[PDB]
Image: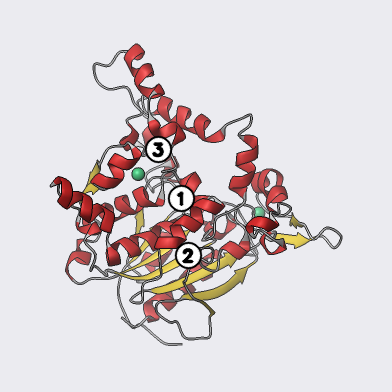
Amino acid sequence: ASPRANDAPIVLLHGFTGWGREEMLGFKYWGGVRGDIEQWLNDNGYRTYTLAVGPLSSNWDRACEAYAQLVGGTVDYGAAHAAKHGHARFGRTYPGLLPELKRGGRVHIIAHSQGGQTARMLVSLLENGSQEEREYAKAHNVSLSPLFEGGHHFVLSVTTIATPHDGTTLVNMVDFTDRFFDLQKAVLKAAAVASNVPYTSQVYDFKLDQWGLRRQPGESFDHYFERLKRSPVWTSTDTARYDLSIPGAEKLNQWVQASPNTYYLSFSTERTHRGALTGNYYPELGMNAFSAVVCAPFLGSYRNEALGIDDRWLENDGIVNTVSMNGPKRGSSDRIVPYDGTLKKGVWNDMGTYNVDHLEVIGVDPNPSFDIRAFYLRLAEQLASLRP
Ligand SMILES: [Ca+2]
Ligand SMILES: [Zn+2]
């Protein structure tokens, strides 16, 4: 029970590789083959909008982009941050999806996977701003984005679904494969090529503008090639891959903390079964093919006791370790409590673990057994029941 206590709008925030509504020919990240989640929510009286930030970027960059997309304006990554990592300070300019957040309004954020880290960071920056950005701005006499001031509280709630709050060991597998096939560098080169091809961005927009991957106006190929080789993007830790790794996720948890003015809900996922002999976990029949063959095996068998990666990390949903989903724990002081019928502020409300994989939970992969429609409508109702 507990009816409508607020009419604050909802924004959907995708995770790693996530694309916007106008990309992928309309195939929705939030809905996939099952439908259009944003539309189902809107048709039911829940004002909903969809955010589309850097699919391969760091949570910091994605948070800054999310902020601009919400209140409108030109993306400002921060002069200190831009200088530190070697990329442009300013980005794209947006009209604003919810400028009402600038004058009292509040918003519910529903995020999937990496989106969970971005949402938490946006809240932390809004609330505390960035001391480093403030000091840098005053010391060099440059402008400061309101986002780094602190004292803002327009986010009412953050709901994470299958979010790797403590990271995912999948990155560890990528580290091993790096000795040969370097996945990140390959993805970047592909993005570099695409940035120069005409219509590509209409299908999949990499949103890596800050790195200047495309050949500029009168730039010759020769100059272009030389400039790219010198780019710091190839060896940068200012990427989603780093924030998603075990050590990167902890560093994020060290400063991104749960705000006492915001409600936090987490949903965990698993689509595996434990081997009686080894203790290792294997993908159930149904998990999307990609995950089942390429990711699940490593996720369900990789251990590193010295780093704290024990048997409790083997259960997974094909992409992320389940134990990493209930809330930040590694390098975190956040509190996680089991949902007891009453949602609380400043803590993670563990809404439970669901038998659906990483892609099925957003409809990208089919699973007739999963009533995706009901899951999101039921979530919307709970968010609407929250007391401001
Ligand atoms: Ca399936
Ligand atoms: Zn950055």
Disc 1 to disc 2, how far (Cα)?
Answer: 18 Å
Horizontal placement of 4 versus 364: left or right?
Answer: left
Is residue 62 toward the left or the right of residue 300 in the image?
left
Decide: is 190 above or below 242. Answer: above
Q: Is residue 135 visible?
A: yes
Give me the C-alpha separation between circle 2 and circle 3: 23 Å
Label 3, residues with CA under 10 Å away: few <14, some 14-19, many ≥20: many
For the C terminus, the quadrant is bottom left
Q: Which is nearer the N-term, disc 1 or disc 2?
A: 1
Residue at 65 percent across and 48 percent down: it is 291
Q: Residue at x 41, y 36 (%)?
A: 203
Disc 2 within 8 angstroms of ligand 2 (CB): no
Query: Type of residue at label 3?
Result: Phe
Q: Which residue carries the number 1 mark?
A: 28
Q: Which residue is mark 2?
A: 160
What kind of residue is marked 2? Thr
Vertical position of residue 112 compared to residue 26: above or below: below
Q: Residue 370: x percent and y percent? A: 61, 65
Q: Which residue is mark 3?
A: 206
**Residue in view at x 40 percent, y 70 percent:** 258
